[PDB]
Amino acid sequence: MSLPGSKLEEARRLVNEKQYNEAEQVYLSLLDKDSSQSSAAAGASVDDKRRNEQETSILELGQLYVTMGAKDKLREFIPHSTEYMMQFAKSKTVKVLKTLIEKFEQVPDSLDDQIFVCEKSIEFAKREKRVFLKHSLSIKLATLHYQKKQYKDSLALINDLLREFKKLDDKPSLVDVHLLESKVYHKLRNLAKSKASLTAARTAANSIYCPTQTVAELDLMSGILHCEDKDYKTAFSYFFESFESYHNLTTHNSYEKACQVLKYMLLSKIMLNLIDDVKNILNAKYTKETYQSRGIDAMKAVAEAYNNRSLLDFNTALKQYEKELM
Amino acid sequence: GEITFDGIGGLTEQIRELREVIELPLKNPEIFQRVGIKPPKGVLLYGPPGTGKTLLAKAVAATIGANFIFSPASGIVDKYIGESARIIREMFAYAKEHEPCIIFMDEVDAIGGRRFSEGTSADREIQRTLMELLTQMDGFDNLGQTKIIMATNRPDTLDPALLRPGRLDRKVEIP
Amino acid sequence: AGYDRHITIFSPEGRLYQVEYAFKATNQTNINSLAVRGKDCTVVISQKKVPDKLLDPTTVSYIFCISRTIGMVVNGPIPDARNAALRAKAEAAEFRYKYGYDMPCDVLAKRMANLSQIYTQRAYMRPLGVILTFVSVDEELGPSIYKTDPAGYYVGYKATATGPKQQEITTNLENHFKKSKIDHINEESWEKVVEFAITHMIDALGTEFSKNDLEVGVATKDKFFTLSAENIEERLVAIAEQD
Amino acid sequence: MTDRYSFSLTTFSPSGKLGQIDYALTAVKQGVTSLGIKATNGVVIATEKKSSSPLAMSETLSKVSLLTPDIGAVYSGMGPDYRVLVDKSRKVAHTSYKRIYGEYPPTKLLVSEVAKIMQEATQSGGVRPFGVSLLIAGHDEFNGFSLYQVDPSGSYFPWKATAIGKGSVAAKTFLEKRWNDELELEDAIHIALLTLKESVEGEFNGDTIELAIIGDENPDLLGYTGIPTDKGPRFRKLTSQEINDRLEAL
Amino acid sequence: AQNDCNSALDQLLVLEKKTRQASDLASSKEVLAKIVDLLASRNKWDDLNEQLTLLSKKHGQLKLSIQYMIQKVMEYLKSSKSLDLNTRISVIETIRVVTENKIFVEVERARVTKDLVEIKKE
Amino acid sequence: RDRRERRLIFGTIASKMSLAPEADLDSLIIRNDSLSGAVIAAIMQEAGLRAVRKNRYVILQSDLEEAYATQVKTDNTVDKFDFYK
Amino acid sequence: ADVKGVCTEAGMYALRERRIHVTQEDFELAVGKVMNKNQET
């Protein structure tokens, strides 16, 4: 018809049958015209029920757009359509604003495009009453800089946000920034700075209730610093803690988390000279999962290349396994 | 011991609990060692001494062929420099040589009080004694082929230190 | 005033010494009880022992039939149990005349709780020691279990236990209900409902008990009945008919 | 034979205090975190639901009782004292006002009626005094939405938000900062979950929060679907699913 | 034919009363020898074996009576070989009176295991 | 000891003794709320020791549970406090 | 007594960050620590 829900179905069919660009023409036309239930907010359409659905169209385009270089069109559309959300409730603005930068970063491919959207959300939010969490968005920008390889630029911003947090009760955000603050420090070659920051994330995490996964993730960083600052034993023990918990989560652990602990666990033993125990992880499948990849094959190959006292075998793994491993 | 363990059966419940804490680690350290949890520490018998508690303590010693070490707690109370340190030390050293062994502490209130009223008259000799037992326990030396069994009528003049796990962990009651 | 346990008044700590001691040593009288819910029944198993051969065990009662349809399981001693029974019985009967309707478990529970509380504040009476589990198969809710406890606190259950094998009973039922995705088992005949009860009982308390060592009270729609001695053995043999 | 106890069991101490009130208060401090908020577009009260057992109903359990139709109460203290007190408050509220002035007592007037029960009990012997503190949150059409505190002695004072139980002061800090009047009821529900997450750690859900609002109408809360004659209730207790829905709403 | 089987079955119900499950009467191999040998006669040894195995899961005049009878029937199964050889496995897993968990002691207990284990290795 | 803190102590003692994919922490977090670091370590250690005296080599989440429930009480005390149930 | 505690708490911050003096910064953070204690639930 012309009502929002029908126009969702029809536009969605436009993506499958043809292309995202075709769907986009339909979506634009649903804003521009097509009389819909309750009060107008585009001069012909809703932008409340119209906006919940608008999260879903932005998302659908948004994954492809950064890769495609159709990015520019994706970049314009959100700023224009933000002023819709302002004409509805405080809660509605809060929910939409926060999502969008995260939606893009599930499939990132144009660090530049993501940066540009985010700076306007930070100006826009100020016009409502929100100045608490504009810094929480400034973490989102910071992760993008880290990836650009701009540790110096991220350093300069990140500290300032940390200072705000602890006298606005943005305490769940504080754990996030402390972990990131560490990653920045670690790369710049301040191995000392990273441990101290992390100990603060740890104090902060235990101040509040939080997810299982977060807690284990700091512990992942703790074990990572404990290979660079030595004490393979202490690295072992956290990675052990992370892995048991993920065993009880079973296969409900996210992909990157489970894989990285396991890559690290196998490695720590090889440096420690507990060669036998890499082979035990390998046989075990509640402590390795179903996972095989090049990394898991490299660790097995090096630990074994290590036992026989064999240099030929080491070079062989290094090279085949290289892209993922190194 | 001078009285049999199978012959005092009809005291069955107490007999079985005492076998399972004492006999199995002493004969076979190997099982406790494989799991990676330590062998048991110290055992308390509490409830009446006059129901034949005493008989049970002798009786466990008889089956293991352990050296039974009967201690008068007051006799551990010499009024000279270090004689009192010396006795605890001798008792333990000899337990290790003569292991397996039962070290049986008769009415623990005198080497393991709580204080008279928080005050002191002679209840610091009690503290001097008591720190030495806690020290051997906490130490690098570990209880597993030397077993210590504490006995007292009432648990209401045992020290809080002892009542805390890791200086006694097994507490058998007489039912 | 006086003191905080020579007469019933607040403790230094805001506690009440008398209600906490009423919880403890009134279930250690050689009594252990459980109640589980049927599909169209409610089952209670409760221990009940006689130490003489000269004590007629019929008069020995600790499941009482409050009305023709209502049962009340008492955990705690016969001096107390009859003060609560007299109150229960009276309340049941009064309700029946005045409001024209049979007495629900929940209403009886609530009324008795508030009354005990008043006796808790009194300085010339005690709270009763007893723990009272009120059972029937209501036509206004299905099979029901509601339990009051001695502090003036009371709350509804779907399955309950008392005596220090509380943990054992609970865990066996919890795991079972999480798997089956129901807190009531489905079976018509009372017989199969008592067998379900026994299964969880035997495992949990780790023993089986004689006819005269048990007492089983069954709630049905518009009846409550106690099982005769032979009837309680029939059931214990019937699971062993399977074995 | 029979009682002779008429000597007051609440008595003065050398400092000017009252032993029984001091004791009773210790219990209240140790009791369950409860708060009350006036959203200005309503009143939201939340209290901790708890369970005794997973095999136990918490439908029967009483942590939020409707004292009169437009008014709810919640507490920290001693559960049994609370239950009886609610009863005497319900009774007098119904007999003495609901066809005498033809409506419920005003909130302030009902706080005074509770206050009196507790004070009778403090003055007089044979019985120890109530050990409780209430937060009476309300609506009356001649005073708007209100929040009061009722103390164990029966001292009361007006509030526009508060918390009592364990961990009060910090709970008030988060509430003070987030709400400063003119706020949607929904939003006050959101703020309230946030204050309590920081206050209670170990395990947190909306299945351990029991939430009531006075701040709505349905036709169902006139109690009839015909032609109005009166306004009727505005008390509405939410079910667990609705609360999880507001926990999902940022 | 039926009559001799009945005297085994009715005499089993007498024996169930007989057995010892509290401090009542008395625990006898005398009754069980009447049942198991004359049922072997009515029927055959293989048939005896399956019916008997189910009966043992309930009482049994204290389990040593049952353990002795289980060894005789077992020797016949082995003697014939084929599927009766299989049947030896089945019987021993079903009930534990020759792999007994009520007591660990006996020579018959061990013997019956050694024969099953030897056939499995072979 | 806050919730993230208890969690670690179960894990650390649990490393030292027999463990398997059953040794469910989620269960435990409900079972223990804020007991000292001394107390959590004491209990976890004792339960492995007690299972092994009951002639179990294996430790499971089931095993910890049966040992614990025995030690914690022998008398029956109805819910928690008189303040809230 | 608190003014003396502020300096000593400020000092642990200085010491961690391997300074050979204390700074103003440490002192603000230290005041924040004491205020936190006074407010107790």
Image (spheres, coloured by chain):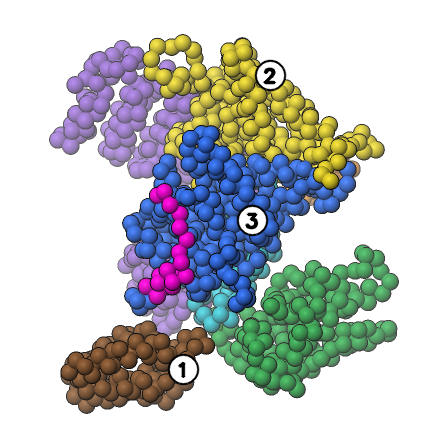
Chain colours: A purple, B green, C blue, D yellow, E brown, F cyan, G orange
Q: Which residue is mark 2?
A: D108
Find numbered disc 2 in the image and state the secondary structure of the residue it sits on. Answer: helix
Q: Chain of mark 2?
A: D
Q: From this view, report whether residue B156 is shown above or below residue E68.
A: above
Q: Are dots 1 and 2 on a single chain?
A: no
Q: Quadrant of the N terminus of chain A?
A: top left
Q: In this orientation, does residue C76 appear?
A: yes
Q: Which residue is mark 1?
A: E26
Disc assigned to residue A42? none
Q: Are dots 2 and 3 on a single chain?
A: no
Find numbered disc 1 in the image and state the secondary structure of the residue it sits on. Answer: loop
Front residue of A72/D139: it is D139
Who's the residue at 34% across and 76% down the image? E16
Drawn side of residue B85 relative to residue A162, left or right: right
> Rounded to the nearest whole Å, what is the CA distance between mark 1 and mark 3?
43 Å
Front residue of B123/A99: it is B123
Drawn side of residue B99 relative to residue D69, left or right: right
> Rounded to the nearest whole Å, what is the CA distance between mark 2 and mark 3?
44 Å
Query: Residue A99's x, y, as percent?
Result: 36, 30
Q: From this view, report whether residue D2 is shown above or below residue D163.
A: below
